[PDB]
Every structure is written in structure tokens, then in C-alpha cells.
Image (cartoon, coloured by chain):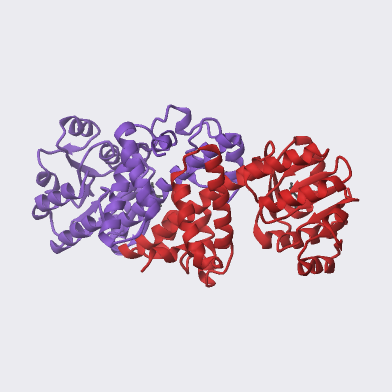
Chain colours: A purple, B red
């Protein structure tokens, strides 16, 4: 299998290296020379343009920053692709954008999946990413051997756009939980309840969630959590702010009522203006900006 | 060891609690000013008395299960002088941290040992003797109390000094309320995006957003057939009771000057929903997010 990998950034570069490492022929394009060089150093044949990268490919993977860039990449490359090429978009983009590019691809006789990922650079490098997939089950079956060497988990979420929708809905919940957990630890401290004691209660009770059992925003109860390491990501505020922007687009596009998610979105947008580089659990320290 | 216990408050939690004490071979002296509650308790072996002070006069331990801080205060005022010195008072009511510490001090000024030990698990937990007790006060007092708590309890956790039981409970329940709303928002958003309830369930429960509000209390019928959504939102944990705890959380916020943006937002949402739907499981808040 020959794979064209379009976007060789902080996620794309290690993903593509795992593909090389699993026996695929990987062709590549990135507009940053430092990204393209890094990738050629691990065996990707890099080309000057995306249409050239796509020319001989059975599978085309995108890992790009916005729906607008993904769309312009599709219209740039679709005529260069061979028929029945399989397109996998692993970018995190809106549901609307996902569905538009899916339809554009299939109109050219291609097969297309949305497959955005969770796990970050660390997951990408360790080949433990979780892919949330939208599209036809038979297209996913065909893609499975390409995805497997990048992935710890591959979940079929439904028809085109479902992958994007599942990730966005999970991350909106996550954001709300990280804030609620933070509020809880600060309230407890002002009530004279120790952090270990609250941790022991909540983790054994109905309030338990990853935001506390793994991402505990106070130092001590979970020695590996970002709070014990100057809030080094982990999952940056910048990235969480990005996901919540997409959740707010989805909310606006559907007319949905999402009071806590929208509140969380405003909290993180404001926090990202100052602390975009910190793990999102660092929000515990911005609560008095609220009043 | 077998002990004489006065049980003040024989309502839908106190009655089954008192029944389990009788089953464990304790002599239980009960009082409740609602004769119907008292009659039900007598049927399961509680010796019912004409007045609270009479019930406490010959008791080694006095348990209160009462609706509010004010009723606890009034009860302690009415009975502390009647109890034998160094009687152990356990308050398993859910009341404000401020109120807890006030009644704790009151009990101690009368020569009585006192713990706060509010419970979670509701009436079914009460009947099954699987309640979680979250305890505030001295280690040695809790050591004294353990034989009495065990026949009612699935978990006993020592949370810290007087008031810490109440604090731990109210922090966990605030988090729960926020999570239950956030889960509802996600499921509605999914429905509007065309993502199925089952698919969203599968994702969130396998990802970082997983929590009891989805995995046990799923607010759409289907994915968790035992959840209240499948039974006309019969509680479960009523909106009335969540609204009361949320009130207690807002009291704790106001007493400390803490900042709890989502917890306060969740309190406002539940206070509105409680005006007409006090009787429904708190998962039913999902109704407010749909047209
Ligand atoms: C466990 C994983 C297989 C992919 C792999 O080999 O990394 C999956 O089933 O998604
Ligand atoms: C919860 C208590 C045991 C009492 C029970 O099984 O009812 C304990 O294990 O501390």
C-alpha cells in the first residue's frame, strides 16, 4: 500500500513514521521545510506539491489545521488521485466541513472517511491514538490495516461526520468536567477539606472522572498529573480552546442549547489568551478572574 | 458490640436505617414527630417514644436523620441536656458545612461526642445497608462509632475534622450536577448533529468524558436500560434532592467566597427545573435542552 500523507506537522510526522515502520510506502507533502525534512529523515518521500504526492497513492491521509485548508487540499488533489483512492481525513474540523469534503471526495469516485484522533503527539508517537471514524463500514474495513499501526483504538461512530461529532461532544464534556473538578478542589480547600481527602471521596463516588483520577489539578494525589510538573501538557489549553471553538460552531449550526459547554468555552478562550501553553487543568488557577 | 441507639428522624431514610440496626441486634429508641413515620419504624422493631428527649435519655448513641440544618439545630437544643454525658451524637442529615460545625460545637459544649456523617445511596441504599457514610470529626470518635455505622453501610470514609463529611458530599454532588447537565447537552447536540445516542454513549464511556452520569444515569433511553430515562424519569435521585444539595453548595460558596462558575450555573438551572419537575430524576434536566 502506497500512502500520501498531506500534513507532516507535530501529529502527521510521527503518524507517518509509524506507517513507514509498518511496511507502507509513504509519500508526503508539507509546506514547512523543517517538517518535510524531518519526515524524509524517517523514510517519507516528500514532494514539492500535494498533487504530486497523491499521484501514485492508494490512500491519502490529511492532517491539517482547518476545514478551509482541508477543503482547498481536496480540490487541489482530487483530479490527480486515481479512481477509488481511499481518502482519510484525520484533521479536527467541523462536522459541516467534514461532510462537505466527504461529499466532494465521493463525487470523484473516491472512498472517504473522517477519522479525527485523540491522544496528542505522545499518542501519535507511541502509536496509541484513538480514531473516531465516520463513514461506510465497508470503507472502514478497507482502511483498517492503514489505521492499525497508528492506533490503540478505532471506533466506528456512524455516517460521514460522526467521527468529528463524537470527538467534539466528548471534548466539550471533558472541558466542563475539568472546570468542575477544579472548582471542587478550590471549594474544598476553602472549607478546610484536604485535597487527598476530597480526591479519595470523589474517586470512590459519583463525581469520578478522568479529569480527577488522571488529571488531578492539585499536586499530590496523582503524582503523574500536570499539576505536579508546572502544568506541562498533557493537553494544552490552546488545543482545548480549539476543540471548544468547534463545539461552539456545531452548537451555532444546529441551534442547540448548551449552557455549560458554552460557559466552559468562554472560560477557556479567556484562559488561552494568557496560558495557551499550559495543560488545560491549569484552569484551576484562573477561577478568580471570573468573580 | 450491642448498643442502645436513639434514632431521631424515621422518614424514608431513617426508617430503613433503623431497621438494619434492629436486625444487627441493637436496641433502637426512636422518635419522629410524624406519627406515620414512627408507626412504620415500630413495625420493624424500633421502640418509639413520646418525645425526643425521652428517646435519648437512656442511649449510648444518638443518630439524627433530619431535613435541614435548622431542624438539626432545634433538635440538638431540645435534647442535648437530656442525654447522658459523653453520649455519641451522629448527624447523618445533609446540611450546610456552617450548620454542621455550629451543631458540632453545640454538642461538644454539652459534653457530647459528635460526628457529621451524611450519606449517599438514597432509600435503596438505606434498605440494602450499602450507604456511603462520609464522616467528619475525631479519628477516635469514628473508631467508637464504627460498630454502629457498619450495619447500615457499604462504605465509611473519614473525611477530616468536623464539617468535612458535609464538605466532601457537597463538593462531589456539585460536580455531579454539572456532569449530568453536560452529558445531557452532549446527547442533545449529538442528536442534532445526526450522531446516534448509542454511538455517543459508546464513545464517551470509552473516552475521557466517562462518568456515572452517562455510564449509570444515561439520560436517553436505550443505552443503559436500568437508567431513569427508560422509566419515565422516576427517581433515582430526584430533582428536589439535587436542588437541595446544590443550595447547600451555593451556601458553602457564599460562606467561603469561592468562585464556582459552572457549579453556580448548574445551581441556577436546577433551581428553575425544580419549580415544575421536582418529582423527576435529576437526569430529566435533558428536557430543558430540547424544543
Ligand atoms: C488494538 C488496535 C489495533 C491497532 C494496532 O495494531 O495498533 C485496534 O483494534 O484499534
Ligand atoms: C461499610 C462497612 C461494612 C458494613 C456492611 O457491609 O454493611 C465497612 O466495610 O467499613
Residue A165 appears left or right of B121: left
Residue positioned 16% across, 49% down in the render: A68
User: Where residue B36 sits: x, y (%)?
Assistant: 77, 70
- Looking at this rendering, what residue extends furthest in the bottom direction? B232
User: Where residue A177 sits: x, y (%)?
Assistant: 45, 47
- In terms of depth relative to the viewer, which is nearer, B164 or B142? B164
Residue positioned 48% across, 56% down in the render: B180
> Could you tell me which quadrant the C terminus of chain A lies in?
top left
- Looking at this rendering, what residue extends furthest in the right direction? B58
Q: Is residue B17 above or below residue B168?
A: below
User: Where residue B197 sits: x, y (%)?
Assistant: 41, 64
Residue positioned 59% across, 40% down in the render: A198
- In terms of depth relative to the viewer, which is nearer, B199 or A138? B199
Residue B231 appears left or right of A150: right
Residue A67 appears left or right of A234: left
Residue B54 appears left or right of A217: right
Does residue A36 appear anywhere in the picture?
yes
Does residue A22 appear anywhere in the picture?
no
User: Where residue A102 sits: x, y (%)?
Assistant: 20, 59
Q: Is residue B124 above or below residue A287?
A: below
- In terms of depth relative to the viewer, which is nearer, B188 or A139? B188
Q: What is the number of callouts on the image?
A: 0
Amino acid at each position: 500500500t502506497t500512502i500520501a500523507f498531506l500534513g507532516l506537522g507535530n501529529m502527521g510526522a510521527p503518524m507517518s513514521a509509524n506507517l513507514v515502520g509498518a511496511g507502507h510506502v509513504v509519500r508526503g507533502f508539507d509546506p514547512a521545510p523543517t517538517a518535510a525534512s524531518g519526515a524524509a529523515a524517517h523514510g517519507v518521500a516528500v514532494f514539492r506539491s500535494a498533487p504530486e504526492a497523491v499521484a501514485e497513492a492508494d490512500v491519502v491521509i490529511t492532517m491539517l489545521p482547518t476545514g478551509e485548508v482541508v477543503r482547498r487540499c481536496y480540490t487541489d488533489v482530487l483530479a490527480a488521485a486515481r479512481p477509488a483512492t481511499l481518502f482519510i481525513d484525520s484533521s479536527t474540523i467541523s462536522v459541516t466541513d467534514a461532510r462537505e469534503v466527504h461529499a466532494l471526495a465521493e463525487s470523484h469516485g473516491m472512498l472517504q472517511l473522517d477519522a479525527p484522533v485523540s491522544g496528542g503527539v505522545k499518542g501519535a508517537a507511541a502509536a496509541t491514538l484513538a480514531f473516531m471514524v465516520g463513514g461506510d463500514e465497508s470503507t472502514l474495513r478497507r482502511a483498517r490495516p492503514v489505521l492499525e499501526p497508528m492506533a490503540g483504538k478505532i471506533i466506528h461512530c456512524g455516517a460521514a461526520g460522526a467521527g468529528q461529532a463524537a470527538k467534539v461532544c466528548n471534548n466539550m464534556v471533558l472541558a466542563v468536567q475539568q472546570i468542575a473538578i477544579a472548582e471542587a478542589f478550590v471549594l474544598a480547600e476553602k472549607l478546610g477539606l484536604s485535597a487527598q481527602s476530597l480526591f479519595d471521596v470523589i474517586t470512590g463516588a459519583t463525581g469520578n472522572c478522568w479529569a480527577v483520577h488522571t488529571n488531578c489539578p492539585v499536586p499530590g494525589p496523582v503524582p503523574t498529573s500536570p499539576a505536579n510538573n508546572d502544568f506541562k501538557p498533557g493537553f494544552s489549553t490552546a488545543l482545548m480552546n480549539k476543540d471548544l471553538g468547534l463545539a461552539m460552531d456545531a452548537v451555532a449550526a444546529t441551534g442547540a442549547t448548551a449552557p455549560l459547554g458554552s460557559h466552559a468555552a468562554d472560560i477557556y478562550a479567556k484562559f488561552a489568551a494568557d496560558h495557551a501553553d499550559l495543560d488545560f487543568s491549569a484552569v484551576i488557577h484562573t477561577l478568580r478572574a471570573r468573580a
